[PDB]
Image (spheres, coloured by chain):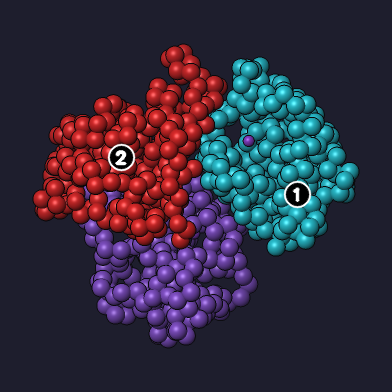
Chain colours: A purple, B cyan, C red
Amino acid sequence: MADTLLELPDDFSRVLAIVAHPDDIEFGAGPAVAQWTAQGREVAYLLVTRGEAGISDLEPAQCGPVREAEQRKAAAELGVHEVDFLDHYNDGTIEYGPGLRRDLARAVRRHRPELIVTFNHHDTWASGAWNTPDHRAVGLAALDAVADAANRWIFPELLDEGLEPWRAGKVAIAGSPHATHAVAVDDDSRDRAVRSLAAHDRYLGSLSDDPPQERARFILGHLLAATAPRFGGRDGVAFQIV
Amino acid sequence: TLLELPDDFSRVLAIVAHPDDIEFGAGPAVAQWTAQGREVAYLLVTRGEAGISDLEPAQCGPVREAEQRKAAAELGVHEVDFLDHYNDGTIEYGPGLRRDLARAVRRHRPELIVTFNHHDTWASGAWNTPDHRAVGLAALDAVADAANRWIFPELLDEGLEPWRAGKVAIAGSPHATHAVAVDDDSRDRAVRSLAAHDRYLGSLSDDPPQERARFILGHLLAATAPRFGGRDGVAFQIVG
Amino acid sequence: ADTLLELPDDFSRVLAIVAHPDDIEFGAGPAVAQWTAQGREVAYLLVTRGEAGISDLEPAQCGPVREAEQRKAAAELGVHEVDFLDHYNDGTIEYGPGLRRDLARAVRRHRPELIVTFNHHDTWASGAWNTPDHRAVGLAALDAVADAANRWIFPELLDEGLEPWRAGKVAIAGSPHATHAVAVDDDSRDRAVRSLAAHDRYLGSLSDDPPQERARFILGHLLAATAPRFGGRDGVAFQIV
Ligand SMILES: [K+]
Ligand SMILES: [K+]
Ligand SMILES: [K+]
């Protein structure tokens, strides 16, 4: 991790966040998303799964629909209107490969993002705990999909689908232990992100008996505060840029 | 500077790709743990049946299974299980391997999992094998899988309740963080354990296997000493 | 950054294993020209024909063009043996036992003392995100050193008449973590420029500068990146394993 984080250059108006599961975006980047949509930038979400194995007391057939509805409400709190879920992937056993790359390249060509946001694909989390193979798989495939989306002859079936090549400008990896850049966040954007994250009610409920609002405030409080020392005292969300 | 591993575990499961991985990377620690009354079991993905140049794998596998079981017995390890249907040299990382590992984790309920180095390079700097990369990665992944009720739901159908192992210790890691001090009786048991891989070590040189074993482990223990307050020991990278 | 060590002169046979045409020329062309000038035997093995690499040519047109370019480029350097694998697809090369086996088969065929690969790390030397083709091929080539040396991994190779072979060393071109270099003289640089420029349609697709100019700039930049960490000598950097 860099000792001085640079400001993320702000030359983009369309953002596509690609993540494995509901909650990845809120934990990793929600306040930045809030800041971006407050400034009039368009943000869409692509989720590979519904996070249907992520609540110990809800079986997957119950949990998926619940978390989908929670993600859609969280999105609406930030003024994100386009939220799409892939089909046919299973929370916890997402496999990296050409199939996933192609499904993500499809989404990149559909949305024509200037910035793509992913979630930490490294072997370890920001904290140093071991990361999951779902995060590793989706982040890797997303990074790889950038060049795939831009190349006419890779996944030629996409052309038949009516989707012409598109080259995204950069990828920003949220929650990386090798963050290089940061996004400064104001108090209103923070408040909004707290509401967004708090909307994952049953999910947070599975991990704490505290009010959803309170856990969310604490969580995003930590995220932002622990950027400041590397960013000249400013609360912000750190990203690794590629 | 390596920290002494904490002593808050009574059951250990070691998960490795092949026979000899444990005896080369972790044997002296295992000996010390079982001497203290801790229960250790081994799970091996393959029988290392491609690892002896003058025995064909059909003959080799059974020879090395027997060598591994004897090595284990020298350290007081009685539970030794081998998976079926993986091939020495071409183990593939994926959910299938993760599931087999999570099964064993749920069966054994280990508080400590021991793995063998999954990094790109050996402790020495040399290029590591895809078997080791695959099994170590899958075992690290399997901790969360074993703990989650909904991942591999077929495990519940088998009567295997979710279980959360507390820590993973990676042996032979070039990024070690902890170590286990080893007394002389434990060093002796570990030498006998490695030497039980008689045909394996006999294929790599003409020295007697126990002499070779004494050399190899003497080196392993001494390499830890400069970073462990001069105590000889086995180094581990701790995950969790 | 450490000073780069001179690569030891202890080999006569080299096998370069890469994903695509141009990998060799971009990563290591001036070293190859230096080796062939010194009478070393160099062979190339290409997993694909880089048939998705030219944005106005569909793979069925681009495959044959790039193969001819790659043979022309090799000839500029006095590389005769250029092998292509079949049934991999440019852009979606999959890492695994099957690729390893194909590579081990080449290693046993050629008996190289030094294997040259292209950067398999997640990032290019520049920090830009590497491709899964490069990650896959480099990784499988590094793994194939042991596979080629082991009688029982891929037992079918024995039946094909390929006895085990242990290569000495792998040198990775274009690595962000280089350790050694090969000094390159003016003659070799000039030959490498001609070799890279032979990728005429490919380079013509990437920028609209004359390919000859473009080749000179790219390879000048390669040689100059190494010089300050190599006693001021122009060279090609490698990570040795
Ligand atoms: K997640
Ligand atoms: K092994
Ligand atoms: K390439």
Q: Position of residue C44 (x, y in %)?
A: 31, 32
Quadrant of residue A190 in the image?
Answer: bottom left
Quadrant of residue B84 in the image?
Answer: top right
Task: Inspect this view and state whether residue A208 appears.
Answer: yes
Q: Observer-nearest residue: C86 or B188?
A: B188
Per the image, label 2 sits on a secondary structure element best described as helix
Q: Observer-nearest residue: B147 or C64?
A: C64
Chain containing mark 2? C
Chain containing mark 1? B
Distance from mark 1 CB to nearest ligand 2 atom below 8 Å: no
In the drawing, does residue A8 fall left or right of residue B92? left
Residue type highlighted by circle 1: Ala
Quadrant of residue A79 in the image?
Answer: bottom left
The residue that disc 1 covers is B222
Rendered residue at 47%/58% (across/down): C2
Front: mark 2 or 1: 2
Q: Observer-nearest residue: C187 or B136?
A: C187
The residue that disc 2 covers is C34
Task: Categorize mark 2 by other alpha carbons within 10 Å: few (<14), some (14-19), many (20+).
Answer: many
In the drawing, does residue A187 fall left or right of residue B108? left
Per the image, label 1 sits on a secondary structure element best described as helix
Mark 2 and 1 residues: CB-CB less than 8 Å, in contact? no
Identify whether B25 is placed above or below A2: above
Rendered residue at 50%/22% (across/down): C164
Task: Categorize mark 1 by other alpha carbons within 10 Å: few (<14), some (14-19), many (20+).
Answer: some
Rendered residue at 37%/65% (across/down): A241
Q: Position of residue B183 (x, y in %)?
A: 86, 49
Q: Position of residue C15 (x, y in %)?
A: 37, 32
Measured Cα–Cα span from mark 2 to mark 1 = 44 Å
